[PDB]
Amino acid sequence: PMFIVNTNVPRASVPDGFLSELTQQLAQATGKPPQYIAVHVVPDQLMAFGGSSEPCALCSLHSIGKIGGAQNRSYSKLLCGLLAERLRISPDRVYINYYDMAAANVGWNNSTFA
Amino acid sequence: PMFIVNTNVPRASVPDGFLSELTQQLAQATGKPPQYIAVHVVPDQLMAFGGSSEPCALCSLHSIGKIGGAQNRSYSKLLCGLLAERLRISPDRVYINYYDMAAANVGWNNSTFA
Amino acid sequence: PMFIVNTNVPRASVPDGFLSELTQQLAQATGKPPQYIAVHVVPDQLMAFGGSSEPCALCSLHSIGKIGGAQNRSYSKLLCGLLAERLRISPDRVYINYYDMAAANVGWNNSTFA
Image (cartoon, rainbow over all chains, first blue to last red; front, side, top):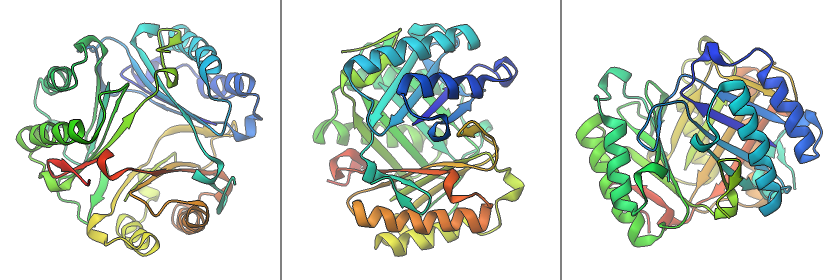
């Protein structure tokens, strides 16, 4: 699984250990081993949500399976929780796009996951 | 809707007001309320289009519905128009990927739109 | 086709000529003319792969067709090869998401490719 967060919150507001916390929590939520979890945080972005430049985040979670109605609700509660607690971003200023990737459409280690 | 623009045009070439203009115009073109429109502009990128480093843009528009052949033509005319007029990027050096997101696959406010 | 790579490798480690090499090699692998190939490299990123911050890359390849099981294996070999040789990123620390785009869902030059 891969999780990306783009945000206008400044780099100095991202706590040390945030990458690790995301890795651990997503391993738990997805059921996948942490060795397969990739995380990417992009602060200091030039962005707006609803026309406002108050703190916000635009995110993606890609995973081979483990994506669906109930699961995505649960991921959204988890991830909005983390972004609120760690980055002080209001859950109503967060979008998370979920992608259920076909194994054949993810490249890794000179091949695909198919 | 979420609109992202990545470009090699420098930050100082992005005019004041550009994110608001995007937000306003996308609300109009998509029919969605401005409060749901998120925009993200990433200047100073290391990129090429057709092997050339002349001004270019790689973009995405994600929306829950309002995505289709005619609509996407109309978005492309609008957005290429804005990138040409405001960032001086030629329309033929612009790619926009469109995504019609399932409501279940967009997280917001601790839940999804499902 | 459009190829984007996000990496924690620093900008000074990206060799001269790298965007052209990507452009050329992807033209060859996809069969599409280089004039239609767009590439984007984003260094100095804050990211982790499998809980660690050694060199890694999170990437996407979007193409109108030319996406599938065998082709994607071949792209992954090529692109992991280039990232290893040029950026010294281990292939096992690289994910590449592949997207087969509908022509109607790609904007270019005030319209779509449909």
